[PDB]
Length: 198
Length: 198
Ligand SMILES: COc1ccc2sc(N)nc2c1
Ligand SMILES: COc1ccc2sc(N)nc2c1
Ligand SMILES: COc1ccc2sc(N)nc2c1
Ligand SMILES: COc1ccc2sc(N)nc2c1
Figure 1 (cartoon, rainbow over the protein chains, first blue to last red):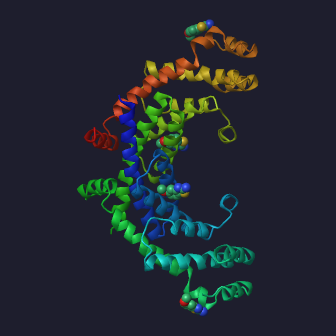
Figure 2: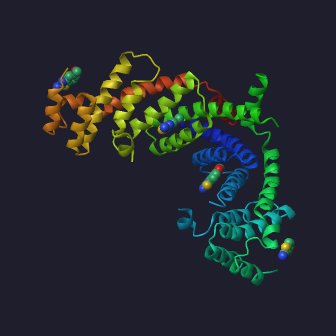
Figure 3: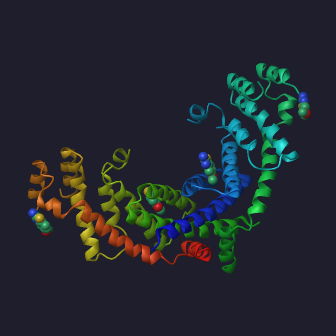
């Protein structure tokens, strides 16, 4: 038994499991299946410890998984480790993924920026909303700070750049990742088995 | 998209990943690759949260993985949760797996029983060695308790039913699991890719 060739086969299989788990995670996110998302996220994270070198494609895959993980924890130890909120961490990942900065990318970025403040207001932590505002900002900045200062959670600006609109735009992006990974090895072989039964 | 057929494909893939990870775990255990074992163990454990119903074969696979996990932690929160040591938990799993109780099964069982006491003596916790002895026992019982009472860690009985002899016998069992799972779908498809390159 050649230990080097066995290690190479384990790395090939980790690559297949990563794409499979990213697909599962995209679907659980799109479907709103929170417990399934949490289980798939735990598996995806553990699996990538079997890879010490990633291709550009695999890097994009792990960063999409980390991005969805932070969005899913948006309203929820992480505070003490990163010193920022989950939506601010989603913003950092989003602004660094190797992807085109098209109209959809900008729309999602702006929705996350405003929702990073609004989720703190929704939770009743207005001091934290101001600290998130200072870290992000740090067209209308003095007006946004006034809305936070005035606890005006349901101001028309917040109603337009809403949590639902952020989730709808992220889900449309998730649909593209889902279609682009639809033909990956593991899910395709698994659907072939299910189709034969049936 | 039929959500039921997608869930069925995810369950088929979890089954393939479980066999693949059990093979990887058997190899890391046999090779003494501790960090690789810990990584594969974390992945195997996370993956099986994607299965709510297991066949008899899958149950045997998860119990072999849990058994190796406890053996690997033999000398190392678990104390407060199970109220026993890792080797005593390995013994409980070993005595309940759906497998033949042949000569090798008995040899491993007896080696774990004595090593559950001896690892406590090796760590200098002689009070714990006596508590392990009382829980397991609880041909010569008064003699074994005297050896523990006398801190006679290197008594010929302990030298014969040694940690090395326990690991050699468990590794011979691991070789059978490894050969029996050698042709499972994921590792075989992965070795085929590596062979094509080479
Ligand atoms: C590949 O999936 C994931 C999902 C969540 C996380 S958090 C982290 N640091 N790495 C990952 C990877
Ligand atoms: C940046 O564009 C917008 C969109 C919606 C609203 S509601 C409001 N008060 N200001 C704006 C600005
Ligand atoms: C399938 O692999 C494993 C490995 C370790 C553990 S601990 C636990 N409760 N379940 C498992 C499963
Ligand atoms: C159960 O068989 C054995 C094997 C080795 C030894 S060394 C000793 N003192 N007693 C025994 C008993």
